[PDB]
Amino acid sequence: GMDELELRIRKAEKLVQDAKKEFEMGLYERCCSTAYYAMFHAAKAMLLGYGRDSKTHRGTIYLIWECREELGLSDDDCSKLSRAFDLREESDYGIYKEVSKDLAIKILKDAEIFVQKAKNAVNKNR
Amino acid sequence: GMDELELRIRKAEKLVQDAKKEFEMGLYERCCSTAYYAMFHAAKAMLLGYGRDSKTHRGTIYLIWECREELGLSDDDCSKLSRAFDLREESDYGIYKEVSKDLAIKILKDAEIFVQKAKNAVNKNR
Image (cartoon, rainbow over all chains, first blue to last red; front, side, top):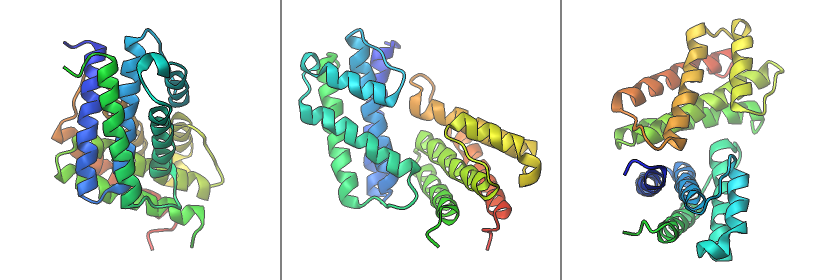
């Protein structure tokens, strides 16, 4: 449908594909930022489906942590989101460090895992 | 040098090129988001060079408006930034609307103009 849960998961899925394409073009910073966004929407979908809500990146990340058991997320899964956020902050707002191919691939693979787990949690792996 | 003014302008310039490549791959939402980031860093460079500072997107946008005369920016130039921010919000955080090729090209061309004007203002068109 056109409900928020469906559209969030669809947005997360599209962003994962966009990030894959950025990676192949060698746009490693852009890949990291997009991959974080995919995870953000997936997190928001999980919070929606389980009657929680957030209005900030940090708020969203901590709620995911708090609700991990119910959501079927491991501690590593929750760390995937924290780390992707921190790396997105560097990609979008940092001016000294450049992001390597190897960092970007790490975040991309984390996004794939995190978004799949989100789909599982909200019964959208359908 | 490795000073903030130089690195901000360099970041803005790189982001404009990244956005051009996203556009060519057909990643229209990603293009808009990247183009806004280019303009953001260019705005921060102009504020730095003219002894002002900001800590929010909206704060940055309003300071650019306030300082436009001194910066050599037209009202349209300031509207380029406001609109690019609003469209970046839709590209990154919206879940209903998709961004067309024609919107993305508009924002891309605005970023090119805005970043050049920023370079002029801070004497980095060198």
